[PDB]
Length: 149
Image 1 (tube, rainbow, N blue to C red):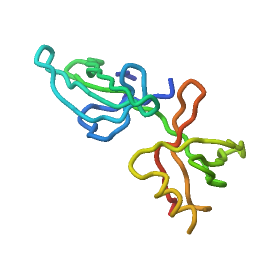
Image 2 (image 1 turned 90 degrees about the horizontal axis):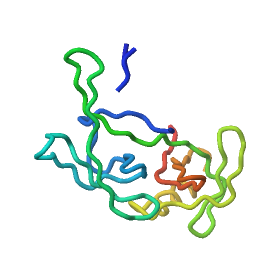
Image 3 (image 1 turned 180 degrees about the vertical axis):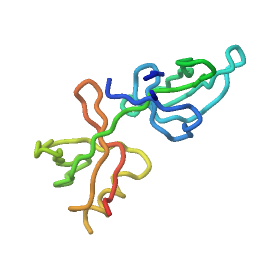
Image 4 (image 1 turned 135 degrees about the vertical axis):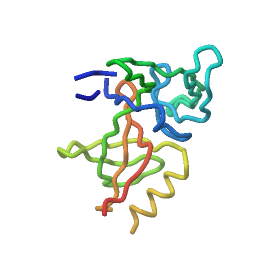
């Protein structure tokens, strides 16, 4: 929103800031966007994405909000990520630890954009590596990485 005018574990993203490859909630599912089009009927943006967990395709159109006179905004929802430290890497999954010390013994890593390989080289050469983590009804998934500098 803004000052208050408004547009779970999701943030509102204006559509002009959405690009191919971004993660969005489509039909309630975390997806990587693979196509952006415009509806002939409504003129709104339409998003086609691949579910990060199930790999199924989902489509959803933007939501048009009009919170104030002459303010008209198309938005989608994106997921909120958690950042965990990486303590160990064993056979496609990692031992991670949260900001408060909570150990996650077997966190799977998404098979996407060479993440396991990029994570391993960054881990091999550990303290500065973080994983970005999404949750699907209790199921956590490492979907990206970050080296803190």
